[PDB]
Length: 274
Ligand SMILES: [Cl-]
Image (cartoon, rainbow, N blue to C red; front, side, top):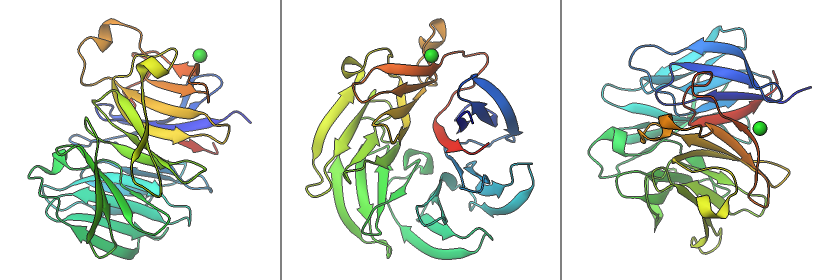
């Protein structure tokens, strides 16, 4: 069947599922006043997990709520993913920053607290990830870094990047890609050395001006989805710059969503069964 894509983004008051082939929105779910969604994810079974700043929740495909976790006052729940083991990972910016692993019943499987030193929760992170050693990769806006945090909260490593790092995603070789937000680029980080292998910007790609480089989603075919979020550039609305691209392994845009009326601003994506 046609591929379907679960999407959401800051400044878009819906999450949606798009039929990739037709480019049609086939399902929406509303966000409330004050909510901000920078993370959506699907389970293999087709359930939908999202963060919304005031919390994170899991719903069925028909819209029934399974479970919800509220962020504490002034905190911002900005991470929400499904780990390879099938459990959910959610996290909130705050003091302390908090990561939870959660089962499909909404029970807490683990908890990690850490302090970033960054006063405004909004200036902390968006999408935290978990690496093969079981530590957490935390990209941070204010300080343009990625930190590696142990489950007890200990700082294990930092690398300095640029821009406003938004997310990380793993490649088959075990390296990761880090989306650098306002730097209009992403980088590849070597597993062993934790050093920058490659920096990719619009000059390395054919077919898209990169605005805020939000979630990156590696594909089995060597390709990549890039969420090209336009909320920081007043010039983006004057043009037809795609909200979402698929690039192939050579860096060419092979497919895109490009309709700022039809599609809201997208910062997060996950393939979904239907
Ligand atoms: Cl296209």
